Image (tube, coloured by chain):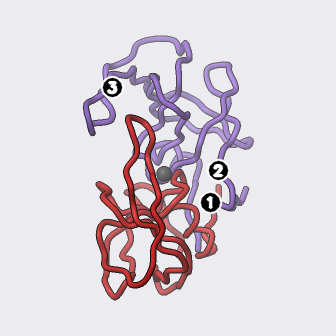
Chain colours: A red, B purple
Amino acid sequence: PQITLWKRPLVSVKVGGQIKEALLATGADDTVLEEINLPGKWKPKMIGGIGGFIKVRQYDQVLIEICGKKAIGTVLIGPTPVNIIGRNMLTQLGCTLNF
Amino acid sequence: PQITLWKRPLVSVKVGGQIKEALLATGADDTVLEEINLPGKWKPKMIGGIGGFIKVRQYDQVLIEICGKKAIGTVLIGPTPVNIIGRNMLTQLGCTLNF
Ligand code: NA
């Protein structure tokens, strides 16, 4: 799909047996989703920085699907005002910016 | 140009007679640049929100150039950790996401 930017690029994403709404964010290094009970082991990770850090759960090699396209990558699980699809997942989708 | 996302999408941008480094950020509504002495009148604007707002200077119909392509739009001038090219300018460049 080609996605124009007149509106916020919000997509439906299938992850962990759920469907969530998330923002495609080329300015974000990582993908962060609000709480979902992903299975298996995780690593602690600290995100943020300005004013302090938030501790989140890093899950590796997680499958997500966006607009019929699948992608495997790290998903951070923790509090976030909006669910963020960041560059680590955008590259797995083949996502590019074009102008 | 086609821009892959293995690295942060940082570009050189010509604005206000200067050249600055800025991030192409599809998750950002607005374009925010650190201090540049743009000419003429401006409107107060408050950005941010989480933990409070920052007052910035809104300049309208400002020309910027990125990778040989020109674009006219609103530029907010104020403190920002990184210079942000947001959707309001990305649409003016013809920028689209593609996967
Ligand atoms: Na972004």
Tag 1 residue: A97
Contact check, label 1 and label 2, Cβ < 8 Å: yes
Tag 2 residue: B9
Compared across the picture, whether A91 is left or right of A83 comes to: right
Q: Residue at x 32, y 22 (%)?
A: B55
| Chain letter, disc 2 residue | B
Q: Amino acid at mark 1?
A: Leu
| Chain letter, disc 3 residue | B
Query: Quarter holding the N terminus of chain B?
Result: bottom right
Q: What SS does tag 1 mark?
A: strand
Query: Quarter holding the C terminus of chain B?
Result: bottom right
| Chain letter, disc 1 residue | A
Q: Position of residue A63 (x, y in %)?
A: 49, 83
Report, in whole angstroms, how far the alpha carbon at label 1 lies from the one at label 3.
29 Å
Q: Position of residue A66 (x, y in %)?
A: 46, 79
Residue B67: which disc? Answer: none
- A70 above or below B8? below
